[PDB]
Length: 48
Image (cartoon, rainbow, N blue to C red; front, top):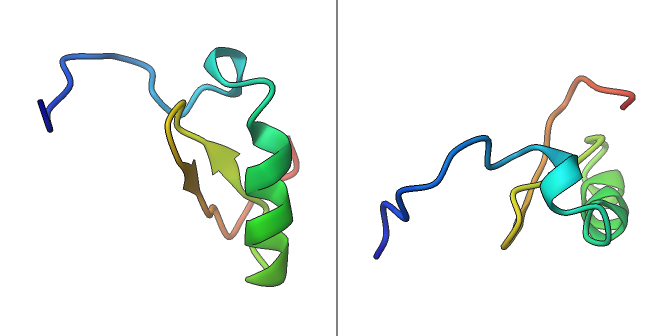
């Protein structure tokens, strides 16, 4: 279960309705944010 056996996880093309919510959280943290198709991840450098 926890290893998932799935590739390219943090591509926003696999989570394009979720990238919005990750930007909203990581913005509060001064990060840019990205989605990993189940949760979010806060990249400190970014800009799409």
